Amino acid sequence: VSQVRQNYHSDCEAAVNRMLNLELYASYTYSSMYAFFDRDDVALHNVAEFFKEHSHEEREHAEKFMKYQNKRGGRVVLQDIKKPERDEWGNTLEAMQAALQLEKTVNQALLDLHKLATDKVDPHLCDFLESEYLKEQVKDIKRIGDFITNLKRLGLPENGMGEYLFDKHSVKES
Amino acid sequence: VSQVRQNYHSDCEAAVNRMLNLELYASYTYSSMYAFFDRDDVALHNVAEFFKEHSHEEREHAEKFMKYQNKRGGRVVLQDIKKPERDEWGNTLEAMQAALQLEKTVNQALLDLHKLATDKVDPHLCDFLESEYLKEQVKDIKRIGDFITNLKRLGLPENGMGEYLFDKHSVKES
Amino acid sequence: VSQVRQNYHSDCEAAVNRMLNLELYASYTYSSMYAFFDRDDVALHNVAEFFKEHSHEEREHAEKFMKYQNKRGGRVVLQDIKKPERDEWGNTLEAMQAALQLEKTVNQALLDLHKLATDKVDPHLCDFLESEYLKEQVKDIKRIGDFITNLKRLGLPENGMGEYLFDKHSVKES
Amino acid sequence: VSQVRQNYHSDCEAAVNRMLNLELYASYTYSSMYAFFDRDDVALHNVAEFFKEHSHEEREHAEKFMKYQNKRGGRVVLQDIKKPERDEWGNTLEAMQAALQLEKTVNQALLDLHKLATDKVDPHLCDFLESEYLKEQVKDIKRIGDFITNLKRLGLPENGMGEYLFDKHSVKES
Ligand SMILES: [Cl-]
Ligand SMILES: [Cl-]
Ligand SMILES: [Cl-]
Ligand SMILES: [Cl-]
Ligand SMILES: [Cl-]
Ligand SMILES: [Cl-]
Ligand SMILES: [Cl-]
Ligand SMILES: [Cl-]
Ligand SMILES: [Cl-]
Ligand SMILES: [Cl-]
Ligand SMILES: [Cl-]
Ligand SMILES: [Cl-]
Ligand SMILES: [Cl-]
Ligand SMILES: [Cl-]
Ligand SMILES: [Cl-]
Ligand SMILES: [Cl-]
Ligand SMILES: [Cl-]
Ligand SMILES: [Cl-]
Ligand SMILES: [Cl-]
Ligand SMILES: [Cl-]
Ligand SMILES: [Cl-]
Ligand SMILES: [Cl-]
Ligand SMILES: [Cl-]
Ligand SMILES: [Cl-]
Ligand SMILES: [Cl-]
Ligand SMILES: [Cl-]
Ligand SMILES: [Cl-]
Ligand SMILES: [Cl-]
Ligand SMILES: [Cl-]
Ligand SMILES: [Cl-]
Ligand SMILES: [Cl-]
Ligand SMILES: [Cl-]
Ligand SMILES: [Cl-]
Ligand SMILES: [Cl-]
Ligand SMILES: [Cl-]
Ligand SMILES: [Cl-]
Ligand SMILES: [Cl-]
Ligand SMILES: [Cl-]
Ligand SMILES: [Cl-]
Ligand SMILES: [Cl-]
Ligand SMILES: [Cl-]
Ligand SMILES: [Cl-]
Ligand SMILES: [Cl-]
Ligand SMILES: [Cl-]
Ligand SMILES: [Mg+2]
Ligand SMILES: [Mg+2]
Ligand SMILES: [Mg+2]
Ligand SMILES: [Mg+2]
Ligand SMILES: [Mg+2]
Ligand SMILES: [Mg+2]
Ligand SMILES: [Mg+2]
Ligand SMILES: [Mg+2]
Ligand SMILES: [Mg+2]
Ligand SMILES: [Mg+2]
Ligand SMILES: [Mg+2]
Ligand SMILES: [Mg+2]
Ligand SMILES: [Mg+2]
Ligand SMILES: [Mg+2]
Ligand SMILES: [Mg+2]
Ligand SMILES: [Mg+2]
Ligand SMILES: [Mg+2]
Ligand SMILES: [Mg+2]
Ligand SMILES: [Mg+2]
Ligand SMILES: [Mg+2]
Ligand SMILES: [Mg+2]
Ligand SMILES: [Mg+2]
Ligand SMILES: [Mg+2]
Ligand SMILES: [Mg+2]
Ligand SMILES: [Mg+2]
Ligand SMILES: [Mg+2]
Ligand SMILES: [Mg+2]
Ligand SMILES: [Mg+2]
Ligand SMILES: [Mg+2]
Ligand SMILES: [Mg+2]
Ligand SMILES: [Mg+2]
């Protein structure tokens, strides 16, 4: 047993390793979306950069879990990072719909980990999730929902001009 | 009778309290519009902020009436602030049409109060309305009319792309 | 169902709308106190400004709830904002006693909402209340209790000189 | 007839000369109050300076009327400036009560001149009174009423300590 370990359940330790993997999985999916929108036959560079940034965010959140694991005296155990579900992402609407879904999947895993931490009476883990993850999750979900509403408004997937305008106005220029 | 009171008719005092209520009512309606355009299924954030600003303006104008009442030695009497007429505002065109109408309602109440002040030979109240309210009222009515003309030009309510472009170009970015 | 909605109970959504109304109610009561202390026959201007500031604070907290509702995919539903319980507030001691009571009422509604969020296993709503509301609530209650103790010490309600001195020394000069 | 004169009734011209005299009369009364509170057996120097400032304000308002008379092509006609009604002013409460009364007298003369200007269809004179005189009049009346309320609260005329504190806290230190 680690000399630092206190009030840290084995189940929580394991679930933290699974969360770490899920963040790396999410980061990798966003990297795929970045590469797709960088294609010469897609060429929506502000959209591409948006997904690149989110890939870097999820990677940082994985790192955060590693650091957390060690602070509590748990042990980081890594698994394969599965490739994304798709090799190509259709268009900005399809990608944002996938992103929404991915953020909700990540959010459900966070909420599940909070339930577990609650069951094991671990308020440090509960606070950590609340402060570092749950708030920013809800904000990302809201942002992407807002985007999907605007892409629909702009006539996606049929309206190319709408897709062009989204890339100029809705995501920051890169 | 207040020690400061001079040339201040009871009828004017009462009409000032009713104006105060109407400004609070207007502020509350604009707050509703703000919340509507902030919805994830509406998501026109520059439009939302425009209405938020106007809500704050009307609230400040209510405060102004309170201060005025006390300066003249009248007594502030508050009533319920009625909820807005609608819970949802359709789209940017419908909301701006409602806003036009609300500003004209407020303007008519100001003009009615000016008539009353004129009938009661109260030049201080007349000047106050002229300087602090009537000018800025006409400017807000003109601005919103200009907006409605542009929203029609942009193909509202059917043309989503037009609605998207209005939010980017016609109202200041937030 | 909103595309962003996740782990957000209908009961919580409704209780958030009721909290929003209660914050607007509180803001309106403080506005009344502001107008009272601005009267020429009361004329305690630093006290008046204290209540004005608290009115603006509660309004900002209402806005916050609106934004929260939308972030979670709930829907803002507004009701009438009831006028304050009194038209006149007696003196600084009576007003601060009313304010104490109002802050405790608001605090109980926050605590009740935290219980509900806890029952519905909503840690995002729990954290939100904890971070944005509960701490600052306890501080406002303490401040007002401190004031009431000093007003009693100063001989309120009989001792006018004490009331004058409170306005100069206990609340910031405006 | 002056080459500049247009739409300027003889009655208005004369009433402007009487207003000029009344402003000089007011200025002189405030000068008396200044000298009273500067006495070694009164010695309330911040109160004294308050009245000195108001004496200078009323003098500037007299000058303003002179300039106005000439701008319209009327002719300045001066009369004796009557000495103040009292040689000694009792205490801060009595003086502020006299000041309230003097400001209301000046305000009634302004309102009477506005009625006359209205009867003679002189909108330039009406605007002049509205912009340069009537607003600031209401503010001075409110300020002095506020003071009288605080002096009563402080136990004037019996409570010397209250009178001392008013001079330190309610009027700006000189
Ligand atoms: Cl180990
Ligand atoms: Cl342990
Ligand atoms: Cl423990
Ligand atoms: Cl342990
Ligand atoms: Cl264990
Ligand atoms: Cl694929
Ligand atoms: Cl997913
Ligand atoms: Cl967070
Ligand atoms: Cl958006
Ligand atoms: Cl289309
Ligand atoms: Cl957008
Ligand atoms: Cl009264
Ligand atoms: Cl009168
Ligand atoms: Cl009159
Ligand atoms: Cl009156
Ligand atoms: Cl009356
Ligand atoms: Cl509706
Ligand atoms: Cl209306
Ligand atoms: Cl104006
Ligand atoms: Cl325009
Ligand atoms: Cl069209
Ligand atoms: Cl425009
Ligand atoms: Cl909905
Ligand atoms: Cl859910
Ligand atoms: Cl859940
Ligand atoms: Cl849900
Ligand atoms: Cl539900
Ligand atoms: Cl009452
Ligand atoms: Cl209460
Ligand atoms: Cl807080
Ligand atoms: Cl204190
Ligand atoms: Cl006492
Ligand atoms: Cl204190
Ligand atoms: Cl001549
Ligand atoms: Cl003429
Ligand atoms: Cl003419
Ligand atoms: Cl003439
Ligand atoms: Cl004539
Ligand atoms: Cl005398
Ligand atoms: Cl007089
Ligand atoms: Cl003025
Ligand atoms: Cl005062
Ligand atoms: Cl006393
Ligand atoms: Cl004072
Ligand atoms: Mg060891
Ligand atoms: Mg284990
Ligand atoms: Mg595989
Ligand atoms: Mg619990
Ligand atoms: Mg907790
Ligand atoms: Mg984020
Ligand atoms: Mg996220
Ligand atoms: Mg996240
Ligand atoms: Mg454009
Ligand atoms: Mg009285
Ligand atoms: Mg009345
Ligand atoms: Mg109703
Ligand atoms: Mg006029
Ligand atoms: Mg305006
Ligand atoms: Mg307006
Ligand atoms: Mg207006
Ligand atoms: Mg939907
Ligand atoms: Mg429901
Ligand atoms: Mg009622
Ligand atoms: Mg926290
Ligand atoms: Mg606070
Ligand atoms: Mg509070
Ligand atoms: Mg609070
Ligand atoms: Mg000539
Ligand atoms: Mg003549
Ligand atoms: Mg004589
Ligand atoms: Mg005018
Ligand atoms: Mg003045
Ligand atoms: Mg004056
Ligand atoms: Mg004056
Ligand atoms: Mg001091």
Image (cartoon, coloured by chain):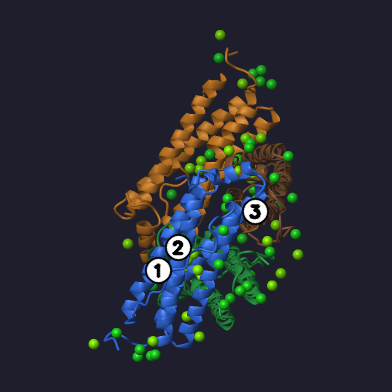
Chain colours: A blue, B brown, C green, D orange
- The answer to whether marks 3 and 2 sit on the same chain is no
Q: Which residue is mark 1?
A: A62
Q: Which residue is mark 2?
A: A27
Residue shown at 28% from the left, 86% from the top? A2
| Quadrant of the picture in which ligand 33 is shown | bottom left
Distance CA(mark 2)–CA(mark 1): 9 Å
Name the element at disc 3: helix
Residue type, numbered disc 1: Ala
Name the element at disc 1: helix
Q: Is residue B143 left or right of residue A107?
A: right
Query: Where's the N terminus of chain B, which quadrant?
Result: bottom right
In the image, residue A41 above or below residue A131: above
Q: Are marks 2 and 1 in contact (CB under 8 Å)?
A: yes
- The answer to whether marks 3 and 1 sit on the same chain is no
Mark 3 surroundings: few (<14), some (14-19) or many (≥20) residues within 10 A? many
Residue type, numbered disc 2: Ser
Front residue of B87/B118: it is: B87
Q: Which residue is mark 3?
A: B30
Name the element at disc 2: helix
Is residue B5 visible in the rendered image? The answer is no
Front residue of B13/C107: it is: C107
The percent coordinates of residue A25 (x first, y second) are: 46, 67
Residue shown at 65% from the left, 23% from the top? D9
Residue shown at 51% from the left, 63% from the top? A84
The percent coordinates of residue C15 (x first, y second) are: 63, 74
Residue type, numbered disc 3: Tyr
